[PDB]
Length: 229
Ligand SMILES: [Gd]
Ligand SMILES: [Gd]
Image 1: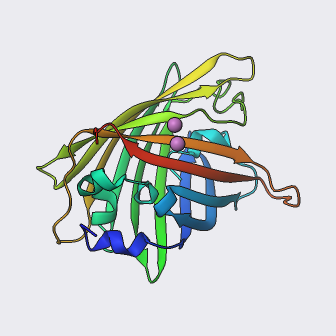
Image 2 (image 1 turned 90 degrees about the vertical axis):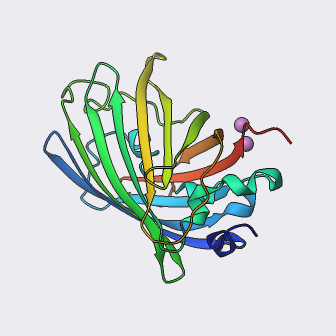
C-alpha cells in the first residue's frame, strides 16, 4: 500500500465524532459513534444532540460531522491525501455559506486516538435569519448526492476542496450551501498530494425508532473518481 496511513484502513475502523457548536448564540453539542470500512467507502454513524434540541437542521451538519473513509480505486491510490496524513491526522477547516442566510465556520481535527478514528469539531455560525430555512427548521430530512472537488495545496502540504450542497426545503425548493475547505496535516511525515479529482459522495439519513433523544442515523458511501484508468 502506497502510504503508511492507508494500512490503518484495510479493515473496519471504529469512529467517534464530537462537535461543539454555537449558531447565532444558540449553543449545542453532538456526539456520534459508529464504524468505517474504507475498502468499500462506507460508514455507519449515529449522532445524538447531547444538549437536548438541535437548533439547526440535522442535514446542515452532515458535511461537518471523515473523508479518510473514501474508497480510492486501485489506479488512484497515490491521490489519497486523507489516509496518508494518518495516524497523526489532519486539520479540516471550512466556511460554509448558506445562500440568502448565514454561514458556518468549522475547525476540526481528524486523527487516530488509539485504534479509533476521531473527528473533533468546533463550529461557529453567524448572520442567520431566526425565521430562515436553517434556524426555522424548514429543511427536509434527506440528502442529495454530491461531488467534492479536490485540488492539491503544495504550500500548506495539504489539499483544498470546494463544492455546493443542495438541501431540499419542505416545499420542494432548494437551500444552497457553498463549501470551501482546507485540509493540512497535523504530523511531520510525508503526505500524498493529489492530482485534481472528486469524491462522489452518497448520504442516507434515517431515525433509530427506539431513540428518544434528538438524533440522526447516517450511512455514507463515497468513492474517488475523475482520473481515467
Ligand atoms: Gd454516485
Ligand atoms: Gd457510489
